[PDB]
Image (cartoon, rainbow over all chains, first blue to last red; front, top):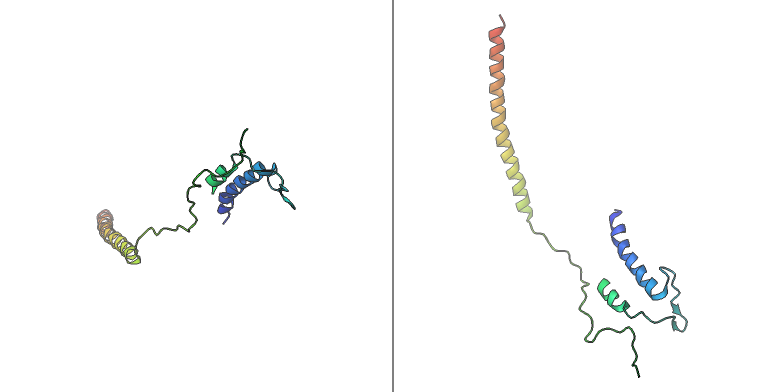
Length: 53
Length: 71
C-alpha cells in the first residue's frame, strides 16, 4: 500500500516530539525509572497532548 | 509564599475526544448505478447508430463518384 506509512509516520514524528519534550530523547528516553519517572512533565505538555489526541 | 505550580489539566477538564470509527456511507444504490450504466450505454448506442448510418451514406456517395469516373 505504502501510503499510510507516510500518513501515520507524521503522527509518529509528533509522538517522538512528545518523548523528546518529556525526556530529551526522541526514541530512547529512559524516562520510566524503577522508582517512578525521572523528571516531571513540562508545563505545556498536557495541552499539546490533548491537541494531538 | 508561592504555591505549587506544575503541569495539570485545566479546571473542568479537557474537551471530549472522538475515538469511534467514522466511515460515512456516501450513498448511491446498486440499482441506481446499474441504471446509469445502462442509460449511458443506450445513449451511446443510439448516437453511434445515427453516425454509422450517415457514414454508410457517405461511403455510398464516394462509391457513386468512383463509378462515374471509372470508364
